[PDB]
Length: 62
Length: 61
Ligand SMILES: [Ca+2]
Ligand SMILES: [Zn+2]
Ligand SMILES: [Zn+2]
Ligand SMILES: [Zn+2]
Ligand SMILES: [Zn+2]
Image 1 (cartoon, each protein chain N blue to C red):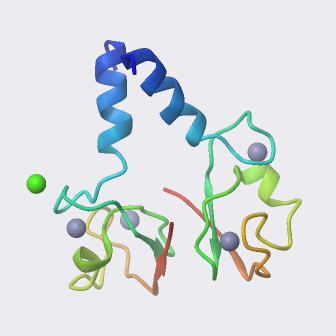
Image 2 (tube, rainbow over the protein chains, first blue to last red):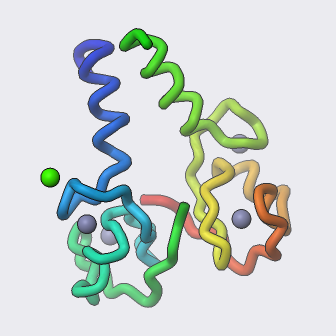
């Protein structure tokens, strides 16, 4: 945001699972499109933890 | 590796692989590759990375 170091941190952090922050995001929720979680953190949710839209598919991403 | 060059690298990685202008905004189903912005996704019927036939172009939130 406010500096190149903060901008760098944001782009590094945005790759990581929003729940555990320990593993890259590896799932996109259909239909809402949120890139939220690694594969393990996506196992327990049936609604998106950001927008609460019912998940119809947990699509693997790379 | 300077902060500025690391940042440039991560910013470039987010760019659509077709136009290299807008950021990636689509996930291809079923292969799951992040390749294109919304506009460029209209031009492809197969994933440019793995050539799998695309069944759905899911918008990233
Ligand atoms: Ca941790
Ligand atoms: Zn996780
Ligand atoms: Zn969502
Ligand atoms: Zn594009
Ligand atoms: Zn692909």
